[PDB]
Image 1 (cartoon, helix red, strand yellow):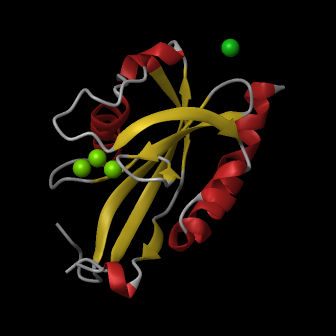
Image 2 (image 1 turned 45 degrees about the vertical axis):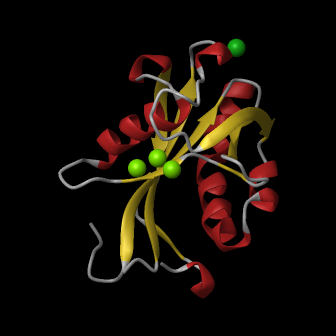
Length: 155
Ligand SMILES: [Cl-]
Ligand SMILES: [Mg+2]
Ligand SMILES: [Mg+2]
Ligand SMILES: [Mg+2]
């Protein structure tokens, strides 16, 4: 499950529309919001894990989205020492998806273990200043990499 360095291989998902917005989801039973992210299971490609977690967490099919971009290397963050439960952080590949189906297709309850209560569209800049602190450096990098593509859709 975990590599030699203590990092869990993980995929993260930025879903956008053609209005310069991204999909912002509220953590189940909490007050904090984030992008979907999920662990890569043994034997999966990153893209496979992404589509699995896409449905598990957001209820979307491959058929509902198109992949616009992905990050070319692993982005890493470490967990706060207090939050460590061995896994000391995640190494993430991030995907940029455009939602092409209707907003109504997003469903947080297709799986037996929902991770989000629900969602809303937010302005492109919003996530970097709103995500939990220990993910902010990764988020800054991700949004910088995806920025030109999302803006192109909104032009
Ligand atoms: Cl549209
Ligand atoms: Mg998750
Ligand atoms: Mg998940
Ligand atoms: Mg998972």
